[PDB]
Amino acid sequence: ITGRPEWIWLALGTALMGLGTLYFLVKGMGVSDPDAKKFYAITTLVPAIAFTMYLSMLLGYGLTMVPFGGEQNPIYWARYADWLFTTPLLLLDLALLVDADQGTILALVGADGIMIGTGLVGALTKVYSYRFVWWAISTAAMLYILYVLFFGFTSKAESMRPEVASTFKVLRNVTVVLWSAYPVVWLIGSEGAGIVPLNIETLLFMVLDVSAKVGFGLILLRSRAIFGEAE
Amino acid sequence: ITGRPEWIWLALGTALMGLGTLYFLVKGMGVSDPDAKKFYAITTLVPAIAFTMYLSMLLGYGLTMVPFGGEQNPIYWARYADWLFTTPLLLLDLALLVDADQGTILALVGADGIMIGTGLVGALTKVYSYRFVWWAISTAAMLYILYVLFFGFTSKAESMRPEVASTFKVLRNVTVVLWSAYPVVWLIGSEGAGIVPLNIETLLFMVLDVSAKVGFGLILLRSRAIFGEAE
Amino acid sequence: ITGRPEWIWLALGTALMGLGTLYFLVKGMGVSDPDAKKFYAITTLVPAIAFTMYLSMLLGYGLTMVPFGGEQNPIYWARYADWLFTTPLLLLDLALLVDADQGTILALVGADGIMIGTGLVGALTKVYSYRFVWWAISTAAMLYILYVLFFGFTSKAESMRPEVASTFKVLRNVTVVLWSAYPVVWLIGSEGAGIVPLNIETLLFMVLDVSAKVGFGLILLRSRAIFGEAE
Ligand SMILES: CC(C)CCC[C@@H](C)CCC[C@@H](C)CCC[C@@H](C)CCOC[C@@H](CO)OCC[C@H](C)CCC[C@H](C)CCC[C@H](C)CCCC(C)C
Ligand SMILES: CC(C)CCC[C@@H](C)CCC[C@@H](C)CCC[C@@H](C)CCOC[C@@H](CO)OCC[C@H](C)CCC[C@H](C)CCC[C@H](C)CCCC(C)C
Ligand SMILES: CC(C)CCC[C@@H](C)CCC[C@@H](C)CCC[C@@H](C)CCOC[C@@H](CO)OCC[C@H](C)CCC[C@H](C)CCC[C@H](C)CCCC(C)C
Ligand SMILES: *C/C=C(C)/C=C/C=C(C)/C=C/C1=C(C)CCCC1(C)C
Ligand SMILES: *C/C=C(C)/C=C/C=C(C)/C=C/C1=C(C)CCCC1(C)C
Ligand SMILES: *C/C=C(C)/C=C/C=C(C)/C=C/C1=C(C)CCCC1(C)C
Ligand SMILES: CCCCCCCCCCCCCCC
Ligand SMILES: CCCCCCCCCCCCCCC
Ligand SMILES: CCCCCCCCCCCCCCC
Ligand SMILES: CCCCCCCCCCCCCCC
Ligand SMILES: CCCCCCCCCCCCCCC
Ligand SMILES: CCCCCCCCCCCCCCC
Ligand SMILES: CCCCCCCCCCCCCC
Ligand SMILES: CCCCCCCCCCCCCC
Ligand SMILES: CCCCCCCCCCCCC
Ligand SMILES: CCCCCCCCCCCCC
Ligand SMILES: CCCCCCCCCCCCC
Ligand SMILES: CCCCCCCCCCC
Ligand SMILES: CCCCCCCCCCC
Ligand SMILES: CCCCCCCCCCC
Ligand SMILES: CCCCCCCCCC
Ligand SMILES: CCCCCCCCCC
Ligand SMILES: CCCCCCCCCC
Ligand SMILES: CCCCCCCCC
Ligand SMILES: CCCCCCCCC
Ligand SMILES: CCCCCCCCC
Ligand SMILES: CCCCCCCC
Ligand SMILES: CCCCCCCC
Ligand SMILES: CCCCCCCC
Ligand SMILES: CCCCCCCC
Ligand SMILES: CCCCCCCC
Ligand SMILES: CCCCCCCC
Ligand SMILES: CCCCCCCC
């Protein structure tokens, strides 16, 4: 484990995702509202999945070597197995908050799968220049997601209860800022141009992951928007 | 790229799926009917997924070598990753058109997963004679799907609006004819008996894919069956 | 095939899953109740999936070698591909029986995916002591599932029709007893401590699989709880 300088950030990430999972699990014990139960189930699964994948990276299972640039490059593939399941769950939290229609939910989840799937292909591609073709396709899929979150959901939240509109607006802004950083870290990190070393890259993804999952969840599960209007 | 004679058909397929995706995306911009939005989302995702997998084959990522018959045989595995997601989406288009019940939808999607999954196992199997055992199981799963589309959905469409009944009947006939060709191309192509060479096999799958996805989508999204009855 | 002593139990399992699939398929022909159709579709898919994965193990495709303990250990990875899809389908049978809320269904299916996913990682892990870390995480996920089936569903079934309450109680008890045996067989078998040899381990999993899928299905599909109350 300790033979890799980035191990400290993988261990911290593992701990923070595990602690986040347990807090949400305990906090959700005393909840019977069927609407609130939906948000607790979605939001608790997110850091639980991330916990297992951070642990796999810490123990060395989620790491492979990819030859490109005449070098064997360490690629943590477990990140994409994490994101494949956690990013659509996070979008479902937002879509259920605004009572989005089914067709829009399917478009979001499908574009998200394309985003993560093409990012994985780009991470494992051995022809250096082709890695950035996949990065560009994946980034186009992300821009579609961000467009929908702004010019489809925002207008839908305003016609909703005030507390669900204000909570959505906050979580929307958090998501757009944090998610946009991921393609940048990829491009300048060891998967892309190799400007930033792997140990610093790992620290950046850990800050982003914890903020986008545990920070996101703390804002959502403390809001009254997750409960139905009741007397 | 150009070192493979089949590259021209992979490049054409990539272009036609990309163009198809963009047309459906633009055409769906001016749509607010929640029913129509469902069909546009399903139908636009189909060629978008196929685009990415054709590109992976063009660039050489979606290709592996499988030893059988005393030879290293080029097997494009990316086809099955495509079909795993696009064939159930196409069946969902048909099932939603006739307002099929949930139990029937699950049976269709499950049989479809078995069809594609066993076809993938057959494509990667190293014992030559066993490849055709998997082909037979996969073909049995397809025949179940075709039976349901005829002796379960057809009777359901007649009790529906006339425009949804006539549109379903057309898309049903297109699907049964085109899908039935796939097991035949597999059997006589490089995955099976090896009668037809890979470059011709690739041309045939490209014609079938574009017809079953973009041609299918053009018929559906030009129909009024996708809109609810409104004044 | 016959070069492996466990082949006899893989062949028996294949036959019993295939026969089970055909019986459920025939029995479900004469069913039009939309509620009953749901249970028949879920319950017939379970042994059909298991059939294909037992066949892959029989023919040698679903087997790999994992080095640990200074030895190349035969690991049947196809079991986890089976369980990944069949265990959530079995939980869906139970959840639909008691009309569970959506949030609870998602929590069950998500915990089940974590259970199977971490068990697969543990089966393929090359550092011997780490294999049991994954076993423990997977077992914690199972205990969560069992808790929900007892202290969330049981109370919900009592407020239901008497026949659905008594049928659920029976299937609940069958599930908790049979599922609990799996982590024990893993721990003492070739994936874990290696006390029980592989051929005996394979026999035990076959008895458990057939009971948990075909036996489970025979109890459910003979009950009147799967039909709506009708005159
Ligand atoms: C509606 C939305 C959900 C739609 C989703 C969008 C999606 C279509 C976007 C594209 C996804 C696609 C790129 C997934 C590729 C997975 C692949 C990286 C797995 C590893 O295989 C890659 C190479 C080794 O580098 O295999 C070496 C050769 C091996 C012999 C490969 C044989 C196994 C194949 C991988 C079998 C295909 C399985 C499916 C891809 C499983 C789904 C994986 C997940 C990442 C989507
Ligand atoms: C309700 C419906 C959706 C049900 C679906 C029906 C489905 C059950 C039908 C059978 C599907 C099954 C054959 C999928 C097999 C995937 C497999 C080809 C992936 C590549 O692995 C094959 C060998 C190399 O040749 O791995 C070499 C050895 C490696 C060490 C393998 C270890 C990884 C395992 C593959 C882990 C299992 C992952 C799941 C199979 C992922 C789903 C893939 C998709 C193709 C279903
Ligand atoms: C809501 C719920 C459904 C959530 C589900 C819970 C889930 C997150 C729990 C953890 C699942 C995770 C451990 C799955 C790992 C699959 C992995 C074993 C496949 C084989 O790859 C392992 C190594 C060889 O030993 O690959 C060698 C290196 C290769 C180069 C690997 C590159 C391919 C990657 C495997 C791509 C990721 C694909 C996804 C993991 C596909 C889903 C598989 C299924 C088992 C979940
Ligand atoms: C909890 C994890 C989250 C919210 C991860 C989000 C990840 C992304 C938005 C990743 C995007 C990428 C691109 C847009 C292209 C480059 C490759 C990716 C996958 C890093
Ligand atoms: C857009 C792609 C489509 C509609 C693909 C359809 C593919 C099939 C219907 C494939 C069927 C197969 C068999 C029936 C057995 C032989 C292997 C397959 C997977 C080619
Ligand atoms: C039809 C198959 C069924 C119902 C299989 C159930 C399997 C389990 C409940 C497996 C549980 C495991 C653990 C709890 C940890 C050890 C590894 C597993 C996956 C065997
Ligand atoms: C979206 C965030 C990207 C900003 C990356 C900042 C990295 C600064 C760290 C110093 C770079 C290390 C280079 C010298 C080793
Ligand atoms: C009462 C609110 C705080 C509860 C404690 C939460 C502990 C989980 C770890 C959170 C750290 C990361 C927060 C986002 C920066
Ligand atoms: C379902 C369509 C299958 C028909 C295949 C027709 C192939 C004819 C092309 C000529 C065969 C090439 C053999 C000589 C190289
Ligand atoms: C107005 C209808 C035609 C629009 C142009 C569609 C261009 C997408 C490519 C379609 C070619 C394949 C059609 C099926 C044979
Ligand atoms: C949950 C069931 C686990 C019980 C396992 C009993 C196995 C007894 C078979 C004899 C053990 C073989 C050891 C000598 C070869
Ligand atoms: C009339 C009920 C029996 C029908 C025959 C079922 C045959 C399928 C194989 C069942 C054997 C396994 C039963 C569970 C132990
Ligand atoms: C490729 C993996 C995608 C599945 C991720 C799991 C979450 C799916 C959310 C589905 C939302 C409901 C759509 C109607
Ligand atoms: C194995 C991958 C299957 C999933 C394909 C994605 C489409 C799923 C459609 C689900 C239809 C809704 C069923 C109720
Ligand atoms: C185009 C939709 C408007 C909202 C999206 C904001 C774009 C942020 C740019 C992200 C940069 C990634 C490289
Ligand atoms: C048996 C259901 C009737 C409709 C299915 C038509 C069968 C077409 C044969 C396809 C040939 C594939 C080898
Ligand atoms: C803790 C929830 C109560 C019901 C679960 C029964 C636990 C059975 C123990 C299984 C042993 C697996 C190692
Ligand atoms: C080795 C660098 C080659 C540059 C390729 C950049 C491709 C980016 C595509 C974005 C449209
Ligand atoms: C090398 C050819 C061996 C023939 C096997 C055919 C199997 C087909 C099974 C269809 C029932
Ligand atoms: C080689 C045996 C090492 C023992 C590790 C046991 C780990 C079990 C963790 C359960 C909390
Ligand atoms: C609940 C605390 C979980 C912390 C265990 C993971 C941290 C790795 C320490 C080496
Ligand atoms: C929108 C046009 C997309 C065409 C790019 C793919 C074709 C491959 C050319 C080499
Ligand atoms: C319907 C009977 C299915 C039996 C075939 C599988 C058994 C393997 C025999 C070698
Ligand atoms: C993106 C930063 C999240 C901050 C988490 C703190 C929330 C406390 C209510
Ligand atoms: C299967 C052939 C499809 C033909 C596509 C043309 C549709 C234009 C309306
Ligand atoms: C767990 C044992 C199941 C027994 C199956 C027999 C059911 C006949 C109704
Ligand atoms: C109005 C809410 C502002 C939230 C933005 C937070 C950016 C990290
Ligand atoms: C909408 C604000 C985008 C912020 C992008 C930050 C990328 C590091
Ligand atoms: C490929 C772009 C299509 C141009 C608009 C077609 C008419 C909606
Ligand atoms: C009555 C519609 C006929 C459609 C059949 C088309 C076959 C390619
Ligand atoms: C229902 C007509 C079937 C046509 C099969 C064509 C196979 C090449
Ligand atoms: C009251 C029903 C008892 C069922 C338990 C069966 C254990 C195999
Ligand atoms: C609730 C009874 C548990 C039985 C466990 C059996 C494990 C072999």
Image: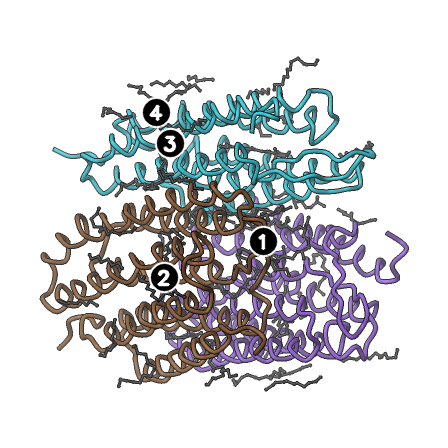
Chain colours: A brown, B cyan, C purple
Q: Are marks 1 and 3 on the same chain?
A: no
Q: Which mark is residue A57?
A: none
Measured in 3D between alpha carbons, the distance from the residue under mark 1 to the one under mark 2, in whole angstroms, is: 36 Å
Question: Mark 1 = which residue?
Answer: A71
User: Which residue is label 4 attached to?
Assistant: B218
Q: Quadrant of the N terminus of chain B?
A: top right
Element type at mark 2:
helix
* Residue found 15% across the figure and 74% down from its top: A230
Looking at the rendered image, the disc whose residue lies closer to the viewer, 1 or 4, is: 1
Q: Is mark 4 within 8 Å of ligand 25?
A: yes
Kind of residue at disc 2: Leu
State the CA–CA distance, disc 4 to disc 2.
Answer: 32 Å
The residue marked by circle 4 belongs to what chain? B
Give amino acid for label 1: Glu
**Alpha-carbon distance for marks 1 and 3?**
59 Å
Q: Secondary structure at mark 3?
A: helix
